[PDB]
Image (cartoon, rainbow, N blue to C red):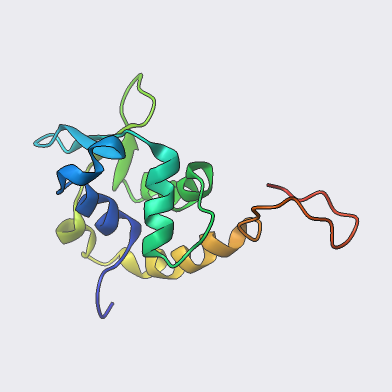
Length: 128
């Protein structure tokens, strides 16, 4: 609680400004259908918000994973990065944010160390 700063709040915030038209924009704002225009940069934007460095979309989608079950966000039928905000911040603050507020930290830790340079500190081969 305290103050919502979850992924969906930030991404929805991007949807409220024409700056990010090349990053994300509304396809049907009333249906809450929105298109992620530049997923790499969208991930970077959210990384920026989450004080994270190298956030790729495949790396960001891990947070979205939960939203699919929370039926917050779905992928539109027969689309790429066309999604649907089934519910907005106001609706999501019904209670399911507790796992999300907890998860964002975790998803940012689940994967590799936001690797920029493929280094071998030990015989590994990282799951980039």
